[PDB]
Image 1: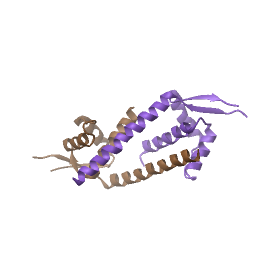
Image 2 (image 1 turned 30 degrees about the vertical axis):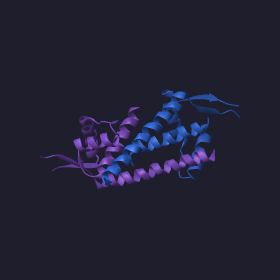
Image 3 (image 1 turned 135 degrees about the vertical axis):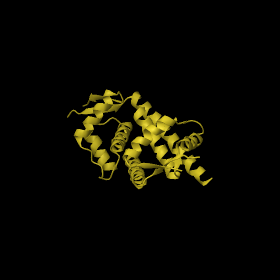
Image 4 (image 1 turned 90 degrees about the vertical axis):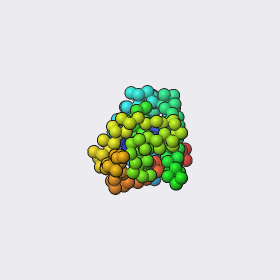
Length: 105
Length: 101
């Protein structure tokens, strides 16, 4: 329901797609539609809006391939931030378990 | 990263209130203990978040010396369940993505 949370989910998925490898928008949508067994088919226009913010923040970069297609790549700024995230969100999952357990105590 | 820092802080607070109604200093203690001192929330940061959450019906407050108690509303429990599901769905989308690769 929280608008800000769907946008976060869509970023998390995308940054993983690019983590598995460099890709083009069409390839990205197919893979998300495939991996979500069809529930999630992102439209190209919202994607281009999202990748626009990411290059602006240096998380990914762009280039051309080979017909010929435009590919996106995860940079270190991205790889690192994606690592920083997993650790920070690991602490959160742990804080919660410590809460749940102290409730039993 | 602020957008992740405020989000993480919100998830924690709302989980404390799921454990039970509690007052601001009691919430900071629990968070400080559950993080073994890593995350020590300041009183003002809580009041800044609880005002946004109370405006949205996610929590409400009441009085019970005397302390101000915060409670997760039905909307909050509900939204928090809908959320944990929507966030669990992502985990599989990703595994299916990594798995398809």
